[PDB]
Length: 214
Length: 217
Ligand SMILES: COc1nc2ccc([C@@](O)(c3cncn3C)C3CCN(C(C)=O)CC3)cc2c(Cl)c1Cc1ccc(-n2cccn2)cc1
Ligand SMILES: COc1nc2ccc([C@@](O)(c3cncn3C)C3CCN(C(C)=O)CC3)cc2c(Cl)c1Cc1ccc(-n2cccn2)cc1
Image (cartoon, rainbow over all chains, first blue to last red; front, side, top):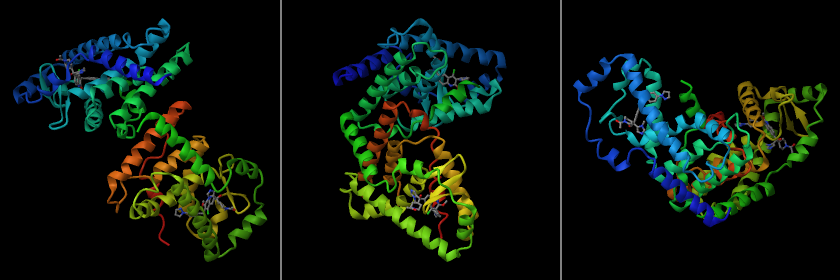
C-alpha cells in the first residue's frame, strides 16, 4: 500500500460520504437556533406509541438507505462477494447511523434535530424507553465533545462498517486488508490534521453493539 | 508527525523496553515450572513485618530503576524539562512496575515469580496487607488473560508514564504532544498485529491510581 494510494483512499471515502451524508452539516448548524416550542413538544408526547415508533422507524430506514449507498461507493466494498456485503451491512449499518446522528446533536441545550426543529429527549417520551433514548443522547454527547469533522466521521463510520470480525463472512482476509487500509487512511489523515488526540477519546465498539441490540 | 514517523516511534519504544525489561519473558516461562515448597513458603511466612517489607522495597526500588532507564531511552521524554520528567516519574513509575509484574504471573496456579521461584499470595502473609496483595493478584490475573505481547506491554507502559493529566506539569502541551503520538502508535500497532480487541479489555483508568493510593509507608 503506497503512500499516495492511502492518501487517495482518504479522498475516496471523504467524497463518498459527502455525496451520501443525507443532511448537510451547515444546514444542521444554522437550524439549532430554531427550537421546538413547549406546545409542539406536547404534541409529540401526546402521540401514541405506534405513531412515534413508526416515524422514527421511517427515519432510520431512510438513513440506512443512505448508508448503503455510502458503502456501494467505497472502493473495495463493491469487490467483496455479495454475501459478505449483506453481512457487513446487516451488522454495521445501524451503528453508522448512530455515529452520523451526532452531527444533528447540539450539546449547548442537549437537543437533536428532528422533523423540522431541534428538540431534547422529551420528544420521544411516547416510545416508553427513556433509558435507550438517554444512552443515545449520552453517546451523541460524547462524539459532540470531540467536534468531529466530516472527514473524521467519514473514515470512522467506514471502519465501523468494514470490520472483518462479523460472523458469517466467507472471504474474511479480503475484508481484513480492506479494513486495514481504511485503518491506515484513518490513522494517516489524523496525522495531517494533527487530530490523533481523538483515538483515545473514542468510545469502545462494545457500546455500539449494545445500543443496537436494544 | 507522519505515519512513517510513528512507525519509527513504535520500534523505538519496543527497543527501549527490551533493553530495560529487567527479566526476560522466556526465562520467566522457564522459571515458571519451579515452585516453592511448603517448607519454603513457611520460611517466608515466619519472617518479620519489617524483614518482608525490606525485601519488597528493595525489589520495588530495583524495578523502578528499570522504569527510569526505560523513560530515558524514550526520545521526546529526554527533551522535556526536568520538573515535568520528575512529576511524570513519581506518578507513573510505580504503576509501570505493577503492569510489568503481570509477566511474572502464572494464571494456572495463581503464583508469581519471587526471589528465585514461584509462590502464591500466601507467600506475603507477614506483610499484614491481605487486601493489597489480593488486589495485585486480581490485577495481574486480568492482564495475563489478554496475553500481552512484549511490545503491547512496551507501548501501554509508555502511555502509563506519558500522561498530560498529571498535577505539577507546566509545559503541559509539550507532554500531550508526546502523549498523543504514543496513542496513535499504540492503535497503529494493534492494527498491524490484528489486536484492537484488547483496547476494550484494558483496565479502566483510575484503576492503576487506585492501586497506588494503597501505599502509605
Ligand atoms: C434519540 O433518538 C433519535 N435521535 C435522532 C437524532 C437525529 C435524527 C436525524 O436528524 C438524523 C440525522 N442524521 C441521521 N438521522 C437519523 C433525522 C433526519 C431525518 N429527519 C428529518 C429530515 O426531519 C428526522 C430527523 C433522528 C433521530 C431519531 Cl429518528 C431518534 C429516534 C430513535 C429511536 C430508536 C433508535 N434505536 C433503537 C435501537 C437502536 N437505535 C434510534 C433513534
Ligand atoms: C504480590 O506482590 C508482589 N508481587 C510481585 C510479583 C513479581 C515480582 C518480580 O518478579 C517482578 C517482575 N517484574 C517486576 N517485578 C517487580 C520480582 C523481580 C525481582 N526479583 C528477583 C530477581 O528475584 C523478585 C521478584 C515482584 C513482586 C513483589 Cl516485590 C510483590 C510485593 C509487593 C508489595 C506491594 C506492592 N505495592 C505497594 C503499593 C503498590 N504496589 C507491590 C509489590
